[PDB]
Image (cartoon, coloured by chain):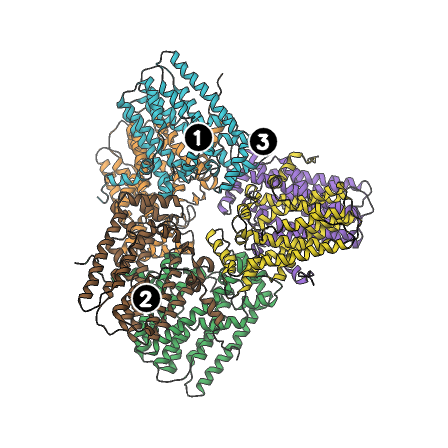
Chain colours: A orange, B cyan, C yellow, D purple, E brown, F green
């Protein structure tokens, strides 16, 4: 007899809701995320059923982060194709991404681990605190110290690597602590990504020529370069202007060589990879079998450094 | 070691919560605070649990408003600038999402496992609400009025239904208030749709006829566009997004000529009836008489 | 056959005529309706033909306004939004042109062949009017006042001269009213140029001093710029196209300091004289006294 | 003694009025319009004097339509050069084009046929009803069915082909009906043009890379592709955004192959050309001499299909 | 010869000086005219020299205003449009700079060589004033209040210090008024900073709270931002450059809650004290009592 | 005891003030300005100490003019790199440039000549009257006559060439008058620059493809071309639109050939170089030694004409 009779969710409607998310999963991609899980599973040996739920959760949370990273940054290309919101609009894309956050949270509930929810929130909370500080610096025009940048990347990479490995740990019968190691793989990953954005014919095709400058981000070398001579304000002022122009991007890229900021970056990645390899050997000299996979993942992720 | 991990300092939390702490220092309605206090007359959650439910709802509330004003591209919010006009869409969006998960770290404090599924399922239905509202907005499809109401059931289901579902989850009473509270959410949304165009308390707060500037197929607007399809003026006006008052004013006039405002007042009437019967429905079945919920039902249709 | 041709449905005609049907549901002057009724006192066209002439003039009228508001980029029109702000320049332009030819399919109904040449020649002179107005606007050449008046003769010749020429073409009287009606068109244009800046009935309708926002070398503006060439303020103000009222206001002040408004009032006076003599001119020569045309001549200079 | 003495139109002034029209006639061009008249005149044999007035009228009405098409569409190139209004301004160009409509109408009056005026209005009225429906769809974002699109192109091509052939018929001593045939040549012309806009190095040079997407137009394959999978809304949403960007245009062009919409388009043009050739043979098996010219015009107009 | 050089005609000088002659036909304060007349009570420059000093100061004055309204992107100036909104930043900038050097060709008329070094050194310090104001504006560094005051000493040193230094250079009295006049320049700047936000005579002239739209770290704004760094609202509001009044209004409210306006009034008080003591300081040392300078000191803090 | 204690200017602050000026001096450049001083010093033989102050003054006044030319014009490239204000903002760059005007004026005071100040003002005043008339024409859309343009360039080049040579004269013990000659070298310089902007692969790399059209400037051939056929208004209307688009710039460049405006320009430069060489020979047939340097500077400055 009711005026309003409540109706069910149709598959047709979910097709709309996931429009921008589905679109992005159609674009060919790195799947670096999967080689890291595969390599850490050589030690944790998470049961196939649980590991598949962990893998779909991370697959989702990944593409959802891109949806919202590319809005917050205003990128123009994503994996060489148009960004999702340049097709669906900032509005529909940022709501697809937010939606997936909770479909992932529904998926995590399938592991029926009681610590799974606390792990998820504590990873997601970490993430938003990384992008919290990053935006604050970017928006306030005050460049962070290299230490601050790193602390910020520990949180940021706390929402994928740390979340996936913590979830695998929570499902594995062993209680080695891998999080300090994976946090370091994250830091090595981002500093590399920051370098490749400014110096790679593979990355000027996929994201854009020096796409980090267009968005204003204080990336790892951009920091070192602004600080190295601070009486020069050419570099920080270029970040302010947020240039889509390429002559400006080229000049900034060239000032950054003249501060030898790309050597600097390359030798820190050298120092951090030594810490990784020694940390892995530490894990193996205590009971864990030789991991070829994760040494190869580490060589892969520095291959242009 | 090259990298020594740092602890999250209280000044950084201040930065993250900046947009959020702003929207909270603005004065608002808190009709939701009395919606909880009325339902708590029947459910009787202890004040230790009720406060957690109340902090969750007030966070999740201010978190949507952070994001909704970006999605809508609102110009104002409770008379004052939208938070993202001070901090930038970038920081507002992030601060908004950050809360979503602090609200979750807060829900776990109830230590109730039925609570985590109630939060996922509520947040999921909220996004299928906005998802379909934005889809019509952007495609310029006009939904049917049944279609609009289903979408409102989900949106008015990530706050109203969340709060009452978490209360039902901390009480032992086996009685479903979810229909009543969802019907209340819809009556609330339909009034917010009318008052957008028709209240000098709402035009002094969100701007003149802001549902037009946003392109939203709101309840009266749907009625007016569908009441005469040969006139494609109102829908064309929604496609342009008019910050100009002389268009907004003209559109409000067209919607009068289609008795969309009489029509709207009339659905709300027919609905409050269903509401005050469903209330007496639960009262006949063992519950004490709830004066307060009757008063919420009539403060939330006080115009019209 | 793959393609079976369809018939033009009445709902599609509704779409085409959308912008047009809008500008017509807005209230207007219809000084042109009384301009026809006054001249019909002398010409005495039967109401069967007069109605066709009247439908043609009211269509061609609303069709220019559709297009003129795009060319000028007007913001308002008779108090209400320009049609193209609801439908988009694209649809408004097309709907405007579409009428131009429906007005022609209407002219053929008189079944008068002198009528088709009167319509071509009128529409041609209208476009040489706007053509030269836009040319000065864009080049920032300021026309001489003789130059401005020649251009107005053509523009005020695709409506006034059209309507009277079609009436003269359905009457047997061999007397030329075209000079009188063209002089009337110019007196009308010059007043519309003054009232743009000086009427609270015209600022409440087209916006404050809208001839400035449009860059138009209007009659008083020409006088003021040419009255002192060492001051390039007024012309520079036309180059910027000021939606800002504080510039518009400043410019209106400058034009007072140059007695462009006294000057303008004075041309209109001198012209109405020529008009009311040319009227008595045709009356001495066999025509009955026309009270109504005297009243149009003075309603159309009622300010000043 | 008069205050205002009325002055004549100078050649100098007409030079201004026709600025955008004259400009466009200076750009080298297809003159496909003239091979169609030439080929249909093999049957109608319109007297040279009349045919020259018909030819100048169509020459004018053509360039005038471009003036206003390129404003309504906001094209950036026209026959490889800048659009007229990118030189003279939307205002001066749309008034030049409107002006020519009536100079053509003055020219038609030179044939001193009484049916010439009714033909002209009935063609022009048809035209504006084609662009009427096209804009309405484009502006309302609701994609037409293939049948609707075609009915719309029957009107659109009713203002050049149909007008020129009807005018020739009205001047010829024979009363064969050629309009059903020419209407079909029009439909074949537009569907081809729609295809070439998205798939031709000759058309990405002359109009722009996928210039139809920039303007949002529901062109013949863009329709078929939106409808073929309607749970995907990537294509229609690209039309909404009206991208000038090329990566977006490339993605849309590529989605359209994956719906096999270019085969679809190519095989309809095949089916319609069969109807043409059979209609021509119908006209010849009834008294008309073999028309090589119009078979060659038809092969020419599909040469990339 | 192909090229025969031409002479600079008086109509061309009219063009160059167009923006300049405009800002001069607008009515202004001329507190600087009475600042000179007060100091001339002690210095007694002959009216033949005083007039040259006065023409230099009134040119250099109107020349900064031409350029400052471009650098700030002011919308208004003394109630009326900024000169560059009529002529374009291009012509305004150039006309502004042109004067800078006509002011110099005017200084040489004093035939005093100490005068040319006083003009260079004054103009140099003006640019180190604006240079550092713009640097903070753009970098979003907030200066310390000592930092702000040093910058004001230079800016209020290319007009105040210029005028008095040129007067001291045409008088034989060996007494330094430069400290007093610089202190007066700062008291003047601090009041202009308060009145921007707090005067209906200043909001009716430059627009509501125009120091916000310009992003300027002005004296009260510095105090408010630095009085609470955990709240990044006011500084974020400066980063956006708000032409919207509802943000400007909100920011003005925040600055009340930080007693930046009480604080500001209090620095001015403490300063006028230093001023009226330094005045009595020079008077004890052989100078006649200067009523007029006491009155300037109190007209230039008449609000507060 | 004072509330405000006044503080000194630090080197740190001057580094900020000169940010845009220092930036521009870092970009590799022509230093044509120095070959002209060097060649005229073969006759004037200005003492090394004075000549160095004259040379630093002109070095400064030069880079300062660029700071403000590139704002007033809204250039996008300067010597092939980004314009200064595209890095520091119209505001900070136009104040750096204005600042340098007076640091130069401080430098001129080091020659301790009493006529040095009057020379400086009279040069700077001339300059601003050249850019005064140029902007007025550009902004008012009314094209100057070739004579007007030239008078305007006599002032414009009165603020570098004339200033540097007048300063050298004021320091030299001889009183030959070189200003009529140098004024003519200026005119030859600008007409050449105007030509090269529209027709040079060296100048389409350094400033931009036909950068003069983007800014609307009535340059020497653009004048001749607008006037040559004045019933065509295509060219002047392109200046109005201020096109950054390249197809528009190409069309305008091509209309300018069809008016044979580049021959015209090239043969005036021929006629003016004859006046130069005959004026120099005049100076030498009166007491001055053969100047190879200034003949080579003149051949250099027409090398593409």
- Quote the CA–CA distance across marks 2 and 1: 60 Å
The chain letter under disc 3 is: B
Q: Are marks 2 and 1 on the same chain?
A: no
Q: Do we see residue F76 in this rendering? A: no
Q: Which residue is mark 1?
A: B192
Query: Percent x, y for residue A239?
Result: 36, 51
- Both on one chain, marks 3 and 2? no
Tell me the SS state at disc 3: loop
Q: Which mark is residue E123?
A: 2
Above or below, A182 relative to C194: above
Tag 3 near tag 2, CB within 8 Å: no
Q: Nearer the viewer, residue C297 or F301?
A: C297
> In the rendering, at what x and y percent does residue A128 appear?
32, 38
Is any atom of residue D125 visible in this view? yes
Which numbered dot is residue B228? 3
Up-down: is B141 above or below F203?
Answer: above
Q: Which quadrant is the N terminus of chain F positioned in?
A: bottom left
């Amino acid at each position: 007899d009711s005026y309003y009779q409540r109706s069910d969710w149709t598959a047709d409607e979910e097709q709309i809701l996931l429009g921008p998310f589905d679109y992005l999963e159609s674009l060919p991609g790195k799947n670096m995320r999967s080689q890291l899980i595969q390599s850490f599973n050589t030690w944790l040996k998470v049961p196939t059923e649980s590991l598949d739920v962990i893998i779909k959760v991370i697959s989702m949370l990944h593409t959802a982060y891109l949806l919202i990273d590319d809005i917050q940054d205003q990128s123009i290309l994503r994996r060489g194709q148009p960004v999702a919101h340049s097709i669906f609009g900032t509005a529909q894309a940022m709501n697809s991404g937010n939606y997936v956050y909770f479909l992932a949270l529904r998926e995590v509930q399938k592991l029926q681990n009681p610590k799974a929810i606390s792990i998820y929130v504590d990873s997601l909370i970490d993430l938003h605190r990384g992008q919290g500080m990053e935006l604050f610096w970017r928006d306030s025009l005050m460049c962070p110290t290299e230490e601050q940048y790193l602390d910020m990347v520990a949180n940021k990479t706390g929402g994928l690597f740390c979340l996936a490995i913590q979830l695998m740990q929570a499902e594995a019968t062993i209680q080695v602590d891998f999080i300090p190691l994976v946090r370091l793989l994250g830091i090595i990953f981002q500093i590399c990504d920051d370098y490749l954005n400014l110096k790679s014919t593979a990355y000027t095709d996929n994201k854009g020529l020096c796409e980090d400058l267009t968005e204003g981000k204080f990336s790892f070398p951009i920091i070192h370069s602004i600080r190295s001579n601070p009486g020069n304000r050419q570099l920080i002022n270029i970040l302010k202007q947020k240039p889509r122009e390429d002559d400006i991007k080229r000049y900034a890229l060239s000032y950054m060589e003249s501060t030898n900021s790309f050597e600097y970056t390359r030798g820190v990645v050298r120092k951090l990879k030594t810490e990784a390899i020694d940390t892995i050997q530490g894990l193996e000299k205590h009971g864990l079998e030789e991991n070829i996979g994760i040494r190869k993942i580490l060589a892969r992720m520095s291959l242009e450094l």
